[PDB]
Length: 186
Ligand SMILES: [Cl-]
Ligand SMILES: [Cl-]
Image (cartoon, rainbow, N blue to C red; front, side):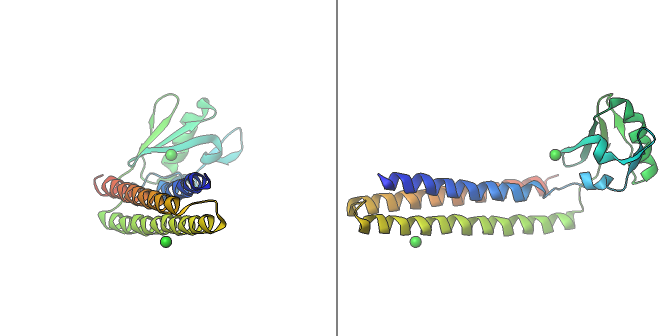
C-alpha cells in the first residue's frame, strides 16, 4: 500500500535527522586535540614553506591525541621540527609512518558547556523527528480521504508511525547520553 510507502519514507526522514545529529556531534570533542591546532604551522617542504595540513592527513582517534600521517614520510623529521618550533607546548612522537601528539582534555568547565551543546542538538533532532511524524500522519489522513487507504489502515499505519517516532526519540536520547558520558568521563 501507499501506507507502507509513507512509513518507509517517514522512517528514512527520521534516520536522516539522526544522521544530521551525529554529524553535529562529530566536532564536539572533549580534548584539545584538533586539526586547527596546526593552522599556523609551516614546514619548508622542498624549499617551499607549506602548511602541515597540506602535507599530511590529520586525525584525532581519541580525545587526547592528534595523529599526523604525512604524504611523504621522509618529511616527518621536518614536520616535528616545525611543530616544536611552533611551541604550542607539544612533544611529538614518531612511529616512522605517523607523528603523534598528546593533548590534555578540555577543562571540565568547557566540558559542561559542550554537554549543553549536545542537548541543543539533541532537542533540535527530536523536533525534526516530530515534524516527520506530523508530516506522515498528515500524509496518511490524506491518503485515506483520497481513497488509497481504509479507516482500518489509517489507525494501523498511524500507530506504526507513532511507534517509530518513539524509537527515534529514544535513539536520540541514547546518542546524547553516550556523548555526554564520553565527554565528561575523559
Ligand atoms: Cl578524525
Ligand atoms: Cl500529529
